[PDB]
Amino acid sequence: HHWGYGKHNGPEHWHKDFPIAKGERQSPVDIDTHTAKYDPSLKPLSVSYDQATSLRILNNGHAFNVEFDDSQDKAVLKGGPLDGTYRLIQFHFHWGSLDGQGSEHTVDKKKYAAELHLVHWNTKYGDVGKAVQQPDGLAVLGIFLKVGSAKPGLQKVVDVLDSIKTKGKSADFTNFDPRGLLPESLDYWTYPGSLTTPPLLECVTWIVLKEPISVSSEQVLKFRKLNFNGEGEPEELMVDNWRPAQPLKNRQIKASFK
Ligand SMILES: NS(=O)(=O)c1ccc(C(=O)NCc2ccccc2F)cc1
Ligand SMILES: [Hg+2]
Ligand SMILES: [Zn+2]
Image (cartoon, rainbow, N blue to C red; front, side, top):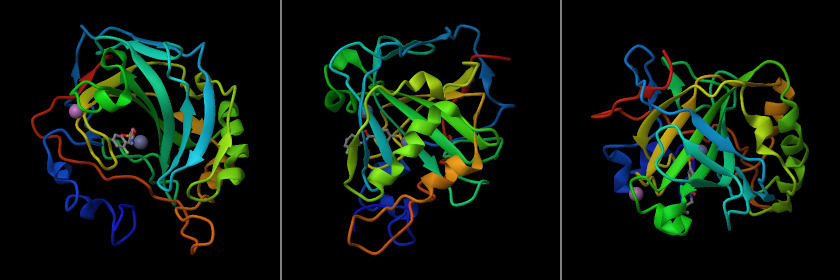
């Protein structure tokens, strides 16, 4: 039926309705640090989230998204391997039922507890709808989460999860600063890829940060209390909403550091 992460409609079944699932530039991938090429020509990342305007948070049945006002250049990503300006439209996470899994990307086969995706779209295309149809329409900043100390900046997100427990629920989420979710360093790996959920469009330039952020066990626990199902339907805990690593094929992962 509609896609999910369960036994009968999970990643291994997506190819039936979305042929692109077996394409040439699918994500996520495993980052082999020893074969990644240090590219000295990669420019540093430029993150300008000072004028970011969050609007709401919603449970779309696959994860929870915090949406931002992208009507104009308020929160943008430039530099790195990007040509142009990409506006932040939303961010979400992928997590597991256990601390030893949750990330989509792996580093030397190592899985993290979760993964944050800050989704941006190329402004030269006018709207996200057009951007998804282009090979460089999207730029997603990936940040690994590992369990340890608490992340203050993540707490506001954690506190409101009860208001959006089931599919379809949304809550006003204004004045949230995404800068509180960034690690100290902006060193990254980059490669051409795709959305990790259907439609699985290959329109993404992936930028994965080397340094994970730490979140407390209690914070991740709250992610695990969300529901895939809507109100009044049988409870299915939202956990393990991650796609396993895809083959790298004819691609090269570049690194901005050595
Ligand atoms: N996990 S991830 O790769 O960062 C990712 C980022 C954005 C989307 C998205 O916008 N989906 C909706 C959507 C997009 C395009 C066409 C139809 C849709 F429903 C999905 C996955
Ligand atoms: Hg595309
Ligand atoms: Zn994602």
